[PDB]
Length: 249
Ligand SMILES: N#Cc1cc([N+](=O)[O-])ccc1O
Image 1 (cartoon, rainbow, N blue to C red):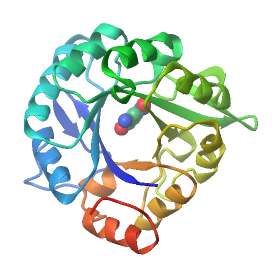
Image 2: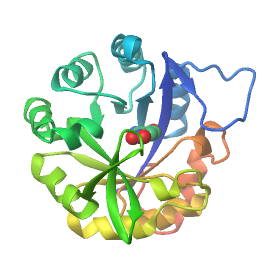
Image 3: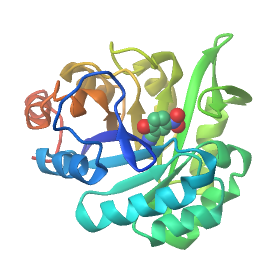
Image 4: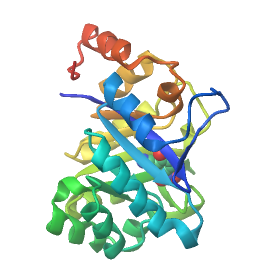
C-alpha cells in the first residue's frame, strides 16, 4: 500500500550522465548535488547505475558511494557490473544501502543469498530486464543484449526464494518510450511474488505513476522526468494522494 517514487541516475567516471539532451549551464554532473536536489524535493530513494570502463570501475564506484553516503540521507542503491560477493560487500561497507544485481544473479543465484544472509535481504535488489519474445516474457542479461532462455515467470519465483529484498522490473519493450510503464508486465509478475516490485522504463507524465501503482507496483523509477524538472515531485505526490495513493508527504 505505501508507494515510493525513486530516481535513477546513470554514472560514468564519477559523473552523472543525462538520459536525454536537455541542458543547463549550472547543472553540473555531480552526484552529490543532484542527490541533494532529489532528497530535498521528496524523492524516496536513489539508484546509481555505473557504466564506467572495466579498468577504473571498481574504485570509481567505491569513491562515488563514499561521497554520496556521507552527504545524503535517503537510501541509495548502487549497481552496474557488480560481478561478485566481494565487490558488493565492499560497496555496502563503504556506504551503499543496497546493491543491485542483474547478470551476475542470473549466472550465480547464490550470490543473492550470500549478500542477504550477511547484510539482510533489504540490501539486495535484483533488476530483471524482460522482453516479449514469441509471445512470452523472457529474461535478458548484458544490458538487454542476451536472451538467457529463462522465463520471467520462473526467474521471479526463484529470485524471491533466494532471498532478494526487492525486484526492479525493467521493460525492454518500454525502453526508448515515454508513454507509460509496462502495466501488462507488472500485472503478470504481481501474483508471482510477495516482494516489492519497482517499475522501470516508460515514464512520461504524472498519470503513468498512478497506473503502475494500480497494476500492483510498489515503487516507480525514472530519471529524465525528474532531472529535467518536467515533473515536480511535490506536485506528483499531491496528485497521487488525491487519486487514492498512499505516498510520503
Ligand atoms: N537501477 C537501474 C538501472 C538498470 C539498468 N540496467 O540494468 O540496464 C539501466 C539503467 C538503470 O538506471
